[PDB]
Length: 9
Length: 9
Length: 207
Length: 205
Image 1: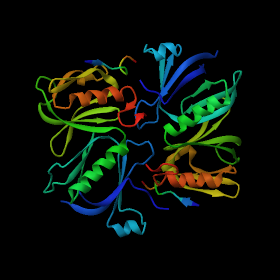
Image 2: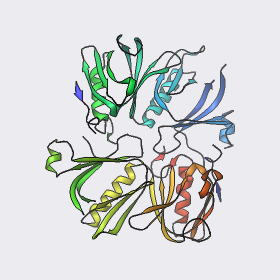
Image 3: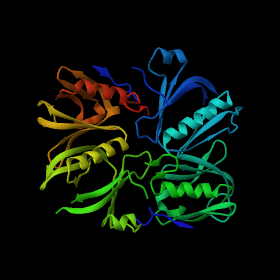
Image 4: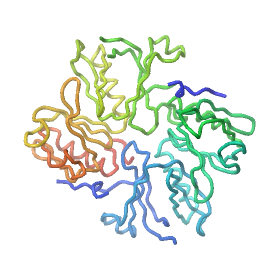
């Protein structure tokens, strides 16, 4: 499953 | 002058 | 100068009542739709002030060809609050409206899915809607919203054999956790997800 | 990870940093700022040094002298103004041109506000930004008055100026307002298009 670049913020 | 159609909404 | 429309034509509204309907975005960067209803095309031709107006400001998705109140060529404008049912005669006019409205609203896609049992979500057939920055699951006729997430609040997601998995994080209180859907379009769903969260429209490139 | 624009820009002392600008939503009035250390830490794939989002954008003001720099662009919000420092007038124009189009309908008009209303008299700049209208002053710009376009009763071009009246809904900003300008007829046409769902350039929304 792909992590979400938006989520880290 | 120009009346606004958006106004009464 | 006449008020523009993204689409206009003869449509049934809610018994059913036939009236000339004008749909347009209230602003150039709107998630909303302004509904402008006239009695007939002439009242609109003669550019008189509409009989009624309404602004749908919480649209979650579109879904055509659901049977409802004796009609088969209907379009649903799905909202967080309510669904708005449009009534068309011809199949192609309904599709024309669905295709035109979709593009105009930005990135609005739908996938027929089956929600797996085990979670807070009701299981069974449903339709997953991506509406720009929001993800929604919708059921029944008229469609009601049974699950909602900001895409930016999803930790993880991905395509799997005959399905698609996504996880909502802490940001989404009681919608947090891992959810499982059956569909043959998981690769399409994941790629759509990959594009949006990085600001790419699969079709238009960067926003 | 895509950008509507990126390049070497100074931000606030001035810190020159590879800036990435993009919309978070395909149809929303927001800019996501991605601050990278350089072009390397960006063209490679590393996560940004810092990020910020601006969600109340109401206009753009280029070509401003600010804190030592000749060529600075102001992104104006209801809450604050973000200043961007460039080296050449062209590099900054590029950024102004690209952002304005991307955000939909964002327009600026250098006007003179007439005394008599709650507004302050003198040179200012009217900004139209999709839904909203704004008067801004100074460097850095501050908003000195705001209206939803839907909340306007009347507007029109007049010999060498422009007029718009705000409805009661506006509260403190209700009433008739007068502006001196040579772009009045251009202003009237823009308002005409927008309140009717027409982009002068793109056609129907």
